[PDB]
Image (cartoon, chains in turn brown, orange):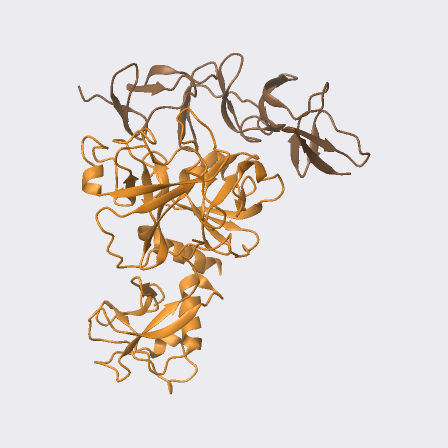
Length: 157
Length: 341
């Protein structure tokens, strides 16, 4: 009663009735989501009631994670317009810095990828992570490019 | 006169206690005569260690300087540093050495239990994000970019110590962080002064698997290319993730005049930053080892050199990693511990 359950990498939770819980449940002031069909902890991008998250073992994550349309700034609670904890939020035409990761979002609130030019500064964003290369020589498209730790490219001719 | 005429500092790899002399503008040692454990405890408490006291004893003077802040007895129940006064030379022929905390001792590929007892893993939303380094029972060193802007509440973080397997870091079993302190100078772009203090809500219990790592004392004389070690959960394989196991990799320091060259970083590295790669590559830090400890062994004690900042290939050397200079921030660390007391 009233504890979690790890079983073959699956995660569950049982309430005071010894029954596995499904849907949103507030455990220790945190919200988890469990699949209605199987009850396992949620995993991966999961649109829900018009609010998009990115679950890992049933706990919404913070940061940038690819979805059906691309990457999104899944942000902490009350970061923009009373958004829930980890809900995807509108983030257009401005940079995002996160654990030393510098993301850039376009007008549609999706993180750009590959080469970009912003305010006269040329950037590059790793396609598989959208992380903006920064801080030393990088091997891109079979060449060499040097980016300052702000991420801005260095011409170097 | 609290930001000068009351400042004490341990010195060297031998922990030689010193007191600042405003009259001559110098750091001086203290003669061993008249000295006992009580004044050692006072000097430790002043240095922000609160109740941590390990050992004090006299050691034959080796620095060679001829001057001492001699203690008084008949001054009355006054400030300890109201008494220490100058003298040409004492008759005890011994200067004081004072250790405020037992640290820098570990048990004698993956790392075995109790080999890096000072390593911790920080969990933002049940996922390993940054490492750390124990310095006292209730203080952990890490990076400022780990706890910046969006992620800055102490309620987001949680720490795990003495556990080697990421799979074994359960939910609700870590230590809750009751405060997050980033360096005021920290610049989000250049990441200069990238160091943060994360005070736990409850003290860490120290055992064979959990132990502090000593801070760098002034006057250590780092050789041009040391033999350090780097620990943390990452991925030796590139295109990887948080490793299931804690690893450790021998690394070699790199001179800042070489690491700022134009084949390496072209002046990206500031005075508060340190490089430690490994020739032939095949070993360096990696993701999840950001905010982890870089340590060395000198004079039989494990010292903390820095913490991870950033890199450009991470085991693709000729673009090695970078760590913040713990020695340069040690005074701010002491001040933050002191004020919290």
